[PDB]
Length: 99
Length: 99
Ligand SMILES: CC(C)CN(C[C@@H](O)[C@H](Cc1ccccc1)NC(=O)O[C@H]1CO[C@H]2OCC[C@H]21)S(=O)(=O)c1ccc(N)cc1
Image (cartoon, chains in turn brown, red):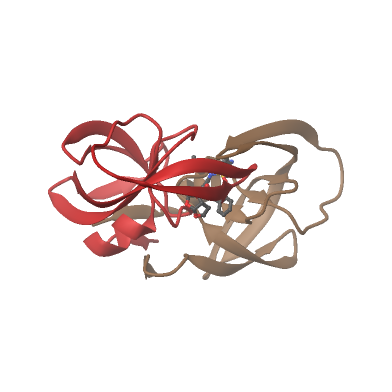
């Protein structure tokens, strides 16, 4: 699709089988979600933003689906105020920023 | 321009006359710049990012130019780990996400 930015670019994604409202976020290097439970081993990571840092769990090889597209990649899970799909996933599906 | 997302979408912008590299950040409502001095009056404000609130100075009616495009808007000056252009500016210059 071709999504303009007059409002927040929010879409419904299925991540690990769960429906989550997500922001398509070119400022996010990696996908970060708050409200999800993913199974198995994870690695401890941290992310940095405006106001400070968030500790996150990194889950690898997760199925991410939205807007008819499908990708597999890592998901950082933690107390973020916004659920974002970042460039780790958007690059994989050929998403570009255009004007 | 067509900007891929396999790397950070960083462009050179002129913001109130000042040349600065900035991140095109679709997940930011607002344009937040740390590395800038802007003249004139400003409004004290607090904005929340991923780690909570930070104090910024809001400058209004700033001319922002990048990649053969121009828009006028507000700039928040304050601490951020990346100088970001938000939707306040990107929506005015017809920026779209495409995939
Ligand atoms: C500041 C960016 C370099 C990084 N952020 C992505 C960014 O798009 C966040 C995404 C975001 C969105 C809402 C709340 C927190 C974070 N937006 C943001 O901080 O915007 C602020 C300026 O405009 C305002 O509008 C929204 C918050 C304010 S981030 O959330 O900290 C972030 C950092 C790393 C990862 N992997 C994922 C996300």
